[PDB]
Image (cartoon, coloured by chain):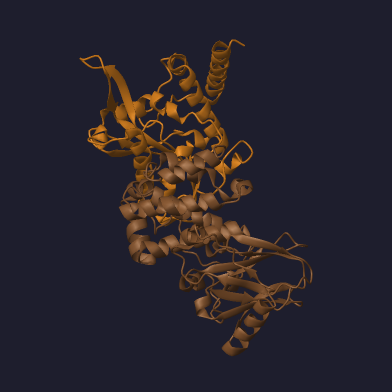
Chain colours: A brown, B orange
Amino acid sequence: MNTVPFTSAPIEVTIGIDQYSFNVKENQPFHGIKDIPIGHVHVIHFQHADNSSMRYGYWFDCRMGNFYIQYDPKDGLYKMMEERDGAKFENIVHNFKERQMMVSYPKIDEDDTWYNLTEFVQMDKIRKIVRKDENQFSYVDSSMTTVQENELSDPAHSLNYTVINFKSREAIRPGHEMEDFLDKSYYLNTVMLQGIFKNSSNYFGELQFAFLNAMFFGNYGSSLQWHAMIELICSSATVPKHMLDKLDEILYYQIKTLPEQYSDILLNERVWNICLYSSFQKNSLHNTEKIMENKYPELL
Amino acid sequence: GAMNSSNYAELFNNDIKLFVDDTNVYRVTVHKTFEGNVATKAINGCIFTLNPKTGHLFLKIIHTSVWAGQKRLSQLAKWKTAEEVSALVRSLPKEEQPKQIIVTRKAMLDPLEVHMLDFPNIAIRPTELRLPFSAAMSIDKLSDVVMKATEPQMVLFNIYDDWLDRISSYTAFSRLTLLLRALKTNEESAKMILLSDPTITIKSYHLWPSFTDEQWITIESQMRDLILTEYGRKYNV
């Protein structure tokens, strides 16, 4: 179990950690989150009480260092930093615990939700999508745009997801125009799995990371990427059996975790109706299909 | 963007563009089998690719052999259209290649777009216009060359005959679409109107009779009357 202390909480802010979140009042004595499960990535995120725009936050993994939050009054936001003085850090952590000013990561022991949402997400891959290599954690916010969005401005702040485009030379072999457009198996298995992602776990990991950015920050380009990566699989006639079954599990927990009131912008009607009812894989997503019907029958 | 009546004169500027109509690419008769079931028999078809400014028609004949052993023929027809249009563009010298291709049916967009990925500066556009190019097989010389073909074949025509020696593209295209509109709404009357006078002939190298200017006026009026009549009949107005 690990800890992320906070120097202070100078402005009123809703703090989130993974799928949990806490209201913290202006200069309330709040000084961190403890009992954070080692073994997964995590994301701590913020929404100021004054600006319900720009949700922002930090992806991190405690194994990779000691991290803390500090409010910067010049830039006006909670910043994640690394403490290199390991002694000085257990010092701050133990004093804040003794003084009991820290919330406990509130995991029900029966609950595998966060594991299920993050099964395939690796910090190393996160830091290639969010290139900022002087930090071991990654910043994401509501407004960051993707590399593909930019092509159609500032690259230092871009989400470098893998570009997927169903009407591109990459996706379509010359002479297999009709075949490859109607059956993306080539694009999926050779171009994307064997070519770029190398295996399905990296693929699944970007897919899950894309979803979580969409959910936690309402990052619209992340949502585009999540849907594209689902559509690519559902529009392929030939998909390894192990991927289909895992995909059904991944999507199930993503749909299960979505806030009910957000289904209108986070869920692309066309993609889900094609994947669940028209695609080659209409029948391979029984759990994802059962939970979509019983929870969002309107969208379908 | 989509062509409509607002951006209509754009068809006659100096940017090369082609209309593509695929309505006659896959043509069948529907008959009953010995056991009483229904079956189709394909007949020869054609892609109707037309430059509305110059009148050049690229009539690509689709021979029934292309369907042999194939499934989802109506879907395949769209991809075969796109394949053949792309090949036509590739066959043309650079300076003759269109800057835009306008498909008369939206279902052609994705097939053409995918086939034209090597031509990203060629815009593929839909249209809101209800163009009558399906009636192209009501032009006897076009139906005839299509129906006789024994193999894939491209036949070139000027759909305007020699009109442009005397009238503008705009006017030429409006005459063509009026004629084809009439032939579509009531072929028999339309054809009657075009030929009632045995003394006005079709030159061997033309598709339509060699009407004088005054005779084109009377003709154009007779087609307009045909089309309006058929509307009242259709709707009881």
A27 vs A188: above or below: below
Measured as percent of width and height from the top left, residue A152 is found at 56, 59
Measured as percent of width and height from the top left, residue B198 is found at 41, 15
Q: Is residue B187 left or right of residue A266?
A: left
Question: In the depicted view, which residue is nearer to us: B232 or B111?
Answer: B111
**The quadrant where residue B65 appears:** top left
Direction left: furthest residue: B34
Q: Residue at x 57, y 87 (%)?
A: A86
Q: Residue at x 32, y 25 (%)?
A: B28
Q: Is residue B158 visible?
A: yes
Q: In which quadrant will I find the N terminus of chain B? A: top right
Count of numbered labels shown in the rendering: 0
Q: Is residue A193 left or right of residue B150?
A: right
Question: In the depicted view, which residue is nearer to us: A126 or A31?
Answer: A31
**The quadrant where residue A158 appears:** bottom right
Measured as percent of width and height from the top left, residue B126 is found at 52, 41
Question: In the depicted view, which residue is nearer to us: A213 or B137?
Answer: A213
Q: Is residue A167 visible?
A: no
Q: In which quadrant will I find the C terminus of chain B? A: top right
A53 vs A29: above or below: above
Question: In the depicted view, which residue is nearer to us: A239 or A152?
Answer: A239
Measured as percent of width and height from the top left, residue B40 is found at 28, 23
Q: Is residue B19 left or right of residue A214?
A: left
A116 vs B68: above or below: below
